[PDB]
Image (spheres, helix red, strand yellow):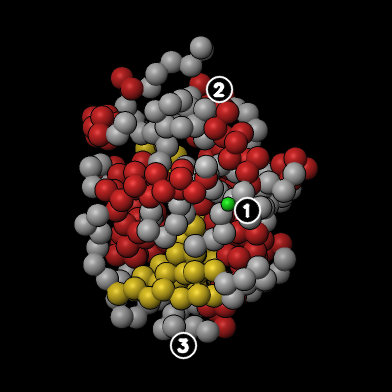
Amino acid sequence: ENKIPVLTRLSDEMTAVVNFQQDIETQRQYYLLERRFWNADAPSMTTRTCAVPTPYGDVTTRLYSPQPTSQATLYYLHGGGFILGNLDTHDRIMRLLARYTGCTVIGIDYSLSPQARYPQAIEETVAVCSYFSQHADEYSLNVEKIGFAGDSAGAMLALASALWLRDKHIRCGNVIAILLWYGLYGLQDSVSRRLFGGAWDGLTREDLDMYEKAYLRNDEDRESPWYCLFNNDLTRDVPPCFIASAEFDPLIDDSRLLHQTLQAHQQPCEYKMYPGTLHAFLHYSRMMTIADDALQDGARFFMARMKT
Ligand SMILES: [Cl-]
Ligand SMILES: [Cl-]
């Protein structure tokens, strides 16, 4: 095997997490199990769980209110390779983003693959944003300014959904920022995909292939511009993007390409690589100060756009 371990290059914090640990419904229940510890001791706050209609049927949302009033609404799309996760697996991340931005965070429990396929989760997200834009007063929201945020597959969904709003001309509020932690955006291969990914992070080429084959309707979708975002128009009208990457993540090149593409067209963005980290590190704030730092950095980016 040409890939070498990244263990000795990981930060002390990251190494501590690696030392701690370690059918589809069963895999989902194990993911809930692995995630439960990391979501403990999350910021206390008001929360409402609301069913929202979509073209596919209702989708559950959770509204986190860190203060009684809000000056923007941040929609959060969780990771899990399109096949795992829910609002509880990312509860702490969402509560912390709400605390740090001072704004309502709305988590979307989008339909998982392989039962759902692309672009269902995007369409559900758009339906949710449209619903809350129409019912803002009822839910005590400020929908004049909105953002999207997500980790891993959720970062894919966040950017894809914002591009869908743009491309289909759907008005849901001014999209002031998109917060993207270690996303994938359509690369099929790359330097980092060949150097990194293994048993330690569950991101071998084989794993990445499996997630894709669960998500797409068929192989033609690999080129669709809301899956391979690099096939969309990234030369204009892209909302400001905060692009965070993990150093030893096979997906880092997807973030680098997104950054470099937006830069080439003077599209607004910030890029930051978090040194010594593996993919998925945003979940480990209870043990890793850098995970909390990455959440704060994204929150600061969002807040700076509530103004400018
Ligand atoms: Cl499924
Ligand atoms: Cl870069």
Where residue 276 sits, quadrant-wise, is: top left
Q: Residue 297, can we see it?
A: no
| Residue depicted at x 23% and y 47% | 286
Q: Which of label 3 and label 1 is nearer to you?
A: 1
Query: On residue 295, which mark appears?
Result: none
Left or right of 3 on screen, residue 47? left
Query: On residue 138, which mark appears?
Result: 3
210 w.r.t. 90: above or below: above
Please, what is the three-letter code of the amino acid marked with disc 3? Glu
SS category of the residue bearing label 2: helix
Query: On residue 115, which mark appears?
Result: 1
133 w.r.t. 103: above or below: below
Pointer 1 residue Cβ closer than 8 Å to ligand 1: yes
Mark 3 → mark 2, Cα distance in angstroms: 50 Å
**How many marks are shown on the rendered structure?**
3
Residue of label 2? 194
Mark 3 → mark 1, Cα distance in angstroms: 32 Å
| Residue depicted at x 67% and y 56% | 119
SS category of the residue bearing label 3: loop
- Quadrant of the image containing the C terminus: bottom left
